[PDB]
Each structure stands twice: as structure tokens, then as C-alpha cells.
Length: 237
Ligand SMILES: [Ca+2]
Ligand SMILES: [Cl-]
Ligand SMILES: [Cl-]
Ligand SMILES: [Mg+2]
Image (cartoon, rainbow, N blue to C red; front, top):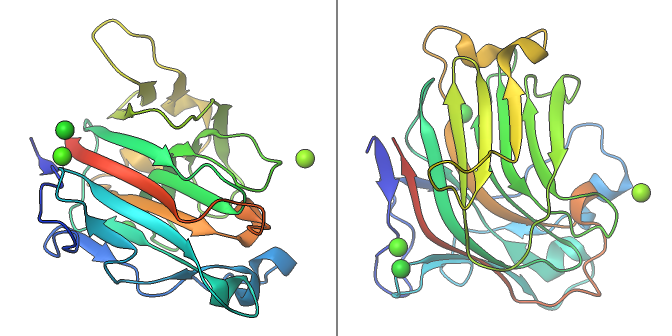
């Protein structure tokens, strides 16, 4: 293995701080439409009521609802960014249970390079609590949203593994991989006019999060909170 977290820490402890950066505040969206204004976007926090080992071998990311005047005040959740960069040829896999498929919630497992001119994003799974957009996987060859391929794919609350293999030829995605299983999504490198993933030394980091509100989650009032993402492990080889 090149990188792994088996999430086997003690109950109530933070994710390993040598492996995970816990994002300390929700992003401020540039030129926001109404759903993306700060008051309509749940907070990200770093405390162990929102991201913590369960002592049973998992990490939990939890979105909560409490008192407040708007979505920002009422809702808090977390986002973790891996402190390890992987490049071409790598196989990324995580075992996850989504107990957070509810109104307003917006869970994802994704890879990121946030370089402002050559960055890119690979969404391995994404589900939208906005009662509108379909769940699925996406390869963004640019961060401005203008050059991507996507595949709708159902996301339910059962335990699954999710795999993305990054090859010179393309990105290949599975749910519950075993030898011989067909990928649910393939994005060939020759299918977009830019492919930063084949630049010399290009690397990406893994991210897990549950966002609340924003364009992807919209109204959380009807949802069931607390809303949990349970992560047994992530492994890269
Ligand atoms: Ca584990
Ligand atoms: Cl286990
Ligand atoms: Cl990055
Ligand atoms: Mg619609």
C-alpha cells in the first residue's frame, strides 16, 4: 500500500492528524447564487462531535442540527482532506456506509488538486440532498465546471466499497469491486481536450465530506439529523 487509514482509533478521537486536515470553516463561494450565500450553507467544524473514530474500526463524519436563525447557524458538519498525494497509476478504494441520504445533506468521496490554473476534481460518489440532482460520479478536467464527464449512478445506504483506478488511459470507477467486475463509469483520457492527470508528476488528495445546504443540498428542514457517513477504511495502491 502507498497510503491507508484503517480508522481504527479510539472512540471519540479525531482522525489521525498526520493523515487528515480537518477543514476549519465552510468555503466562501465566489459570486454566489442565493443557495450558496454563507447563511444558506452549513458550517464545517473540527470537533469530535462531528468527525471522530467510533472505536469499532470506523471514522464518522456527522452533520447535526441545532438552534439558530439560518442554515449556517443551525447546521454543522465536517470535511477531511488527506495529507498524502497520489499520482497516475494509483487505485483508490474506500469502504463507506451512507446514513446521511437526507434532505439538505450532500456527501461525497472525491479526489482533488486545487491548483488555480491546472487543478481538477474526481467525484467517486456524490449524492445531493436537494431533491433534484441525480447522484453519481464525475471527472472534472478543470475546476471551473466547463470540462467534465459524468455518470448517474444510484447511491443507497448499504455498506459499499467505492474504487477509482487512475490509469494513463483513463479513470475507471467501481462499486463493490471484485476481479472481473465491470466498472460503472469509464472516462477515457482522450475523451476531453484537457487531461491534467497526465501532466508530469500530477498528484491529487482524497477528500470525504458531508456538506449541508448550498446548491447541492438546498433546504435541510425536512431532513433527518444527525446524518452520518461511516468510513471503515481508505486504501491506495
Ligand atoms: Ca476500519
Ligand atoms: Cl470492519
Ligand atoms: Cl490539493
Ligand atoms: Mg430539476
